[PDB]
View 1 (cartoon, rainbow, N blue to C red):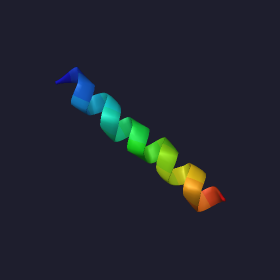
View 2 (cartoon, rainbow, N blue to C red):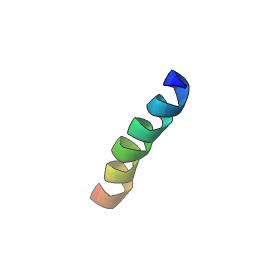
View 3 (cartoon, rainbow, N blue to C red):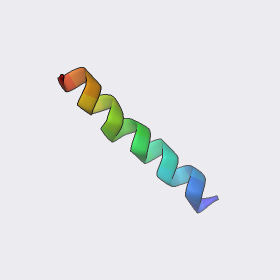
View 4 (cartoon, helix red, strand yellow):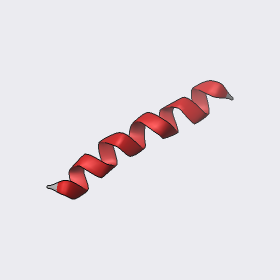
Length: 21
């Protein structure tokens, strides 16, 4: 599932945006 692999990488960048704020 290439789509499932894109959701995981998306959770890493979004997790850094909130932790950065």
